[PDB]
Image (tube, coloured by chain):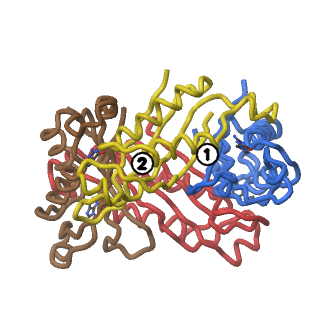
Chain colours: A red, B brown, C yellow, D blue
Amino acid sequence: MDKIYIHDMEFYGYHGVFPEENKLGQRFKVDLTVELDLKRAGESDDLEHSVNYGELFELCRKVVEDRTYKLVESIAENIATDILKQYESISRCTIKVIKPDPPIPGHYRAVAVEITRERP
Amino acid sequence: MDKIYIHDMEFYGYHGVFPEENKLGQRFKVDLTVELDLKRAGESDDLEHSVNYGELFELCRKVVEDRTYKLVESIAENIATDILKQYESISRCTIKVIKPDPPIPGHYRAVAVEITRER
Amino acid sequence: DKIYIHDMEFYGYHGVFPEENKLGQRFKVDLTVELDLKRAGESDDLEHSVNYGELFELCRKVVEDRTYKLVESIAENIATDILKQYESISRCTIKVIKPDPPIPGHYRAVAVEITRER
Amino acid sequence: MDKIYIHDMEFYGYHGVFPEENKLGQRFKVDLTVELDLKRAGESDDLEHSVNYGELFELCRKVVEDRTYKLVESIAENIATDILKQYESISRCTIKVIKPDPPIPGHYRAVAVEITRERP
Ligand SMILES: Cn1cnc2c(O)nc(N)nc21
Ligand SMILES: Cn1cnc2c(O)nc(N)nc21
Ligand SMILES: Cn1cnc2c(O)nc(N)nc21
Ligand SMILES: Cn1cnc2c(O)nc(N)nc21
């Protein structure tokens, strides 16, 4: 379907399995993909009929900054839940939470989770 | 299908919901993807069997520069439509309209809208 | 399963407008050939998979050693010769990229991408 | 189907058909994706129902650095293979083994092989 994106959002967060992670913190990135209809929006030009990009960002920030989890799997899952719940026009969404600097000994760009949630 | 592409067209436009995005303006980017058959163009090596990539660029430039809308949706929608209407050789198209510097307090690369259209 | 060569850069003199044919410009090719790789991945054998080096060479040949009006015909003659010389290739996808075309404006690149198979 | 990614792991190894590639060595890069349900991980916040991203790194490194094959097809095959053996919770995977500086006389970014491997 049609799609709103927010590419490579960046937060500082305290999330992790290790208590050393909890204390120090690290970078956390999020990519978002949400699906709806944009034919109406595009034939109209009135934001009242699509989902507001600025609110979708804020939502993401609350989960990554205003709350702490052990797993990036819980960041992704919460984001997805608040999305579908708060926004009834969005059908599907793919959400990817990225830990560019995890505490692993080796050479790499990033580890990440990605889920894709839908209304039953 | 086979695909023609234009990658990362960059414009300056004055689009936006708030009046201040219309005053100041901002960068807008557009990725173009159009679906058609290029087997004929390939074995012929003759441009009339394909679509001119310049005319495509120009067509989008007109939408992003010569007009102004509240919504990127609306930019995506007019491009898809003006491609389909003007080009019958094209079955299907995908247009993505990127705002890289929207006024959101935060840290992000970009926001965007992608639509895929057909007759 | 899949084999890849990414961002092959060549200098060629392709194009519709006769000035492009004297000046020339950059041409990039993304190659993407499909098959099964279970055979080679257990045997550890270049017999049971495709030579990546030859695939580059074939692309080099079509982009550097001949000239066409269209990028679509670079793409075609590559995809046709891949399916000619390599039976075990189920399918292929060629994306030919013109990064510096003579369009007055600001973009990264224009491009064709075909997918061919027997 | 949900996914754990590991992007652009970098190793130095001595893989190659040519005996010269075998003596000198060169860079090798690996991308990993693995499919599994992460909905329970995302509610419980419990790593046991998911899979350690770190152990995944190590699995890949064993193959690239502790062993030496003639082909990159072999590298991705054993990786996929070893993933499927050890982790029942993982349904499928995709492995891209990249060779960024292969001995091809020309101009290019990288050559590579991607495979996808599932269980019965
Ligand atoms: C090892 N490790 C630490 N935190 C983790 C997380 O959120 N997910 C996974 N899969 N592994 C983790
Ligand atoms: C908040 N906001 C402002 N302009 C917008 C647009 O074009 N699309 C969406 N989804 N949100 C917008
Ligand atoms: C305008 N133009 C010049 N060369 C071209 C090509 O190969 N394809 C298309 N579609 N347009 C071209
Ligand atoms: C030509 N060539 C040299 N080494 C190679 C390797 O490891 N794989 C493939 N497919 N080709 C190679």
Sort mark 1 into few (<14), some (14-19) or many (20+) by Cα contacts within 10 Å: many
Mark 2 belongs to chain: A
For the residues labelled 2 and 1, the Cα–Cα distance comes to 20 Å
- Name the outermost residue toward the right: D66
| Residue D93 x, y percent position in the rendering | 67, 39
Q: How many marks?
A: 2
Q: Which residue is mark 2?
A: A84
Q: Are marks 2 and 1 on the same chain?
A: no
Q: Which residue is mark 1?
A: D3
**What is the three-letter code of the residue carrying label 1?**
Lys
Looking at the image, which residue is at 80% across and 47% down?
D18
Which of the two residues, B90 or C102, is positioned nearer the viewer here?
Answer: C102
Q: Is residue B96 visible?
A: no
Looking at the image, which residue is at 18% across and 43% down?
B83
In this picture, residue A21 sits left or right of residue B44: right
| Residue D11 x, y percent position in the rendering | 76, 59
Q: Is residue A103 above or below residue D110?
A: below
Mark 1 belongs to chain: D
| Residue B71 x, y percent position in the rendering | 21, 59
Mark 2 and ligand 2: say if the CB distance to the nearest ligand atom is below 8 Å. no
